[PDB]
Image (cartoon, grey):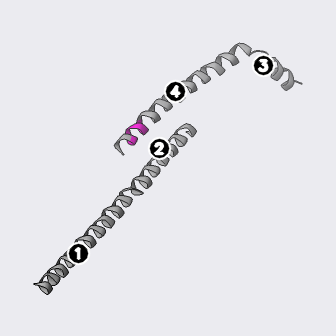
Amino acid sequence: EAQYRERERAETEALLARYRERAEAEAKAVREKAMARLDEAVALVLKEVLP
Amino acid sequence: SKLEAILSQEVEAEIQALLQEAEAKAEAVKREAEEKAKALLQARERALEAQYRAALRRAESA
């Protein structure tokens, strides 16, 4: 029981850390993808709002 | 005497039957205690392994 308890702690921490790192990488990646692609859509919304 | 040795042999046969029954019952007791140590070592190991697996599933879902 002590063996599987410590194995649970070690594996859960080692997997959750990679999940946090993949989350930070995915957020930074989608922001840098969206930022350079911008200013095409502002003309679309500004054309469709105005009469 | 003859019936003297017959009665002594009957006492030896009673002691022999007593010790054989003691061996048989002690073997049965240690056997069933071995199966209960066994199958309990089965049950708690499978339960703790399944707990570890369910913890991993919940962690990857989270």
Labels 4 & 3 near each other (Cβ < 8 A): no
Against A50, is B52 above or below? Answer: below
Q: Quarter of the image holding residue B19? A: bottom left
Secondary structure mainly formed by the magenta segment? helix
Q: Quadrant of the C terminus of chain B?
A: top right
Q: Residue A41's mark?
A: none
Mark 4–mark 1 Cα distance, whole angstroms, equals 68 Å
In the picture provided, is B5 more to the left or to the right than A45?
A: left
Q: Quarter of the image holding residue B61? A: top right
Which residue in the structure is indicated by mark 4?
A: A18
Span of residues in magenta:
A4-9
Q: Quarter of the image holding residue B40? A: bottom left
Please, what is the three-letter code of the amino acid marked with disc 3?
Val
Mark 4–mark 2 Cα distance, whole angstroms, equals 19 Å
Task: Say whether residue A8 is magenta.
Answer: yes
Against B44, is A48 above or below? Answer: above
Which residue in the structure is indicated by mark 2?
A: B52
Name the residue rendered at 76%, 15% in the picture.
A39
* Chain hosting mark 1: B
Which residue in the structure is indicated by mark 3?
A: A42
Q: How many marks?
A: 4
Badge 3 and badge 2 in a common chain: no
Against A8, is A51 above or below? Answer: above
Q: Position of residue A50 (x, y in %)?
A: 86, 23
